[PDB]
Amino acid sequence: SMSLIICYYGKNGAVIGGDRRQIFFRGSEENRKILEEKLYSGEIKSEEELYKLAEKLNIKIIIEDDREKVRKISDSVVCGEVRSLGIDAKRRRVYATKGKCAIVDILNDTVTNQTIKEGFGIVVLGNRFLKKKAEEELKRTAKLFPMMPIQQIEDAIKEIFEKLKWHPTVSKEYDIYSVNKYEKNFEEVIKKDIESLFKYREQLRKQLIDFGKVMSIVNKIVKNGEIGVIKDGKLHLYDDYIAIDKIDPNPKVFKVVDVEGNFKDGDIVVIENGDMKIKGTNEKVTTKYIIIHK
Image 1: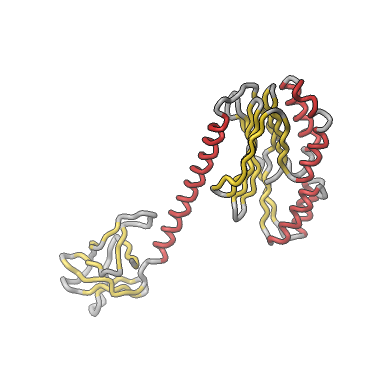
Image 2: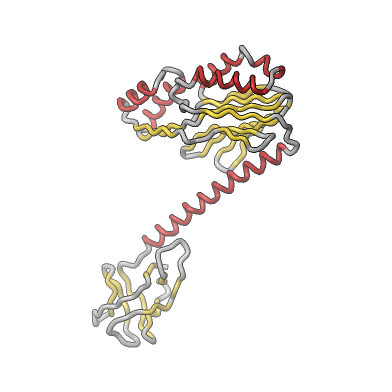
């Protein structure tokens, strides 16, 4: 979630800093909201205040600080991201190279806004409180950045992260990266990075689709039915039914199923309460396969 990213771009290069902290809340949507407002307004000054207020509101907190939010893609490009994963996956990414910066907004699998900037400036992403304080701290050095060596800008940005990291939306560790080369294919590099996000999301989607196929197979298992007729020692299933070799997202399907037991050709196979037997005789029918409704 929203902590702090600070990004400079100018003729001397680009510099980005960001922390790593994510906070997950579990509990009522309304109390969640109350907690976030106080967290992002500056009312909540420490972790102890946060944990205390959360327990009073019946919200469980999970803080995870393994989220790298800024990266260095190459000699010429740095980037950062803020995001909110809820019902919707909301992201705002900043990319920067010497002399240029881009901001891209993404809702789920759609780019909803983009901004490209050339010249020099600063982009601050994060919560209101930290955004404002960083901007306030920045107004004292930001004018000087275009005339500074890169290391001094790094330092100026570190200083701001040192001054603000007491805040509980910030991790203990933060990352600073800079580049001093111009990326000639800036837009392509951004495009490729964004496509990777979409590929990754399409993979998660496939995993969830597969889970749903499996659950759907499990709910379709036959507990009751007249399912077919014995022929050549095999169960020839009726149209409403099919067999599968195992519970899997895309299993081998069978209409004609190897079975064992005391029956003969023309005997009708039934299942009642999940017990497979011969109609009339009531003799037991075993199989390796799983029978499901079409």
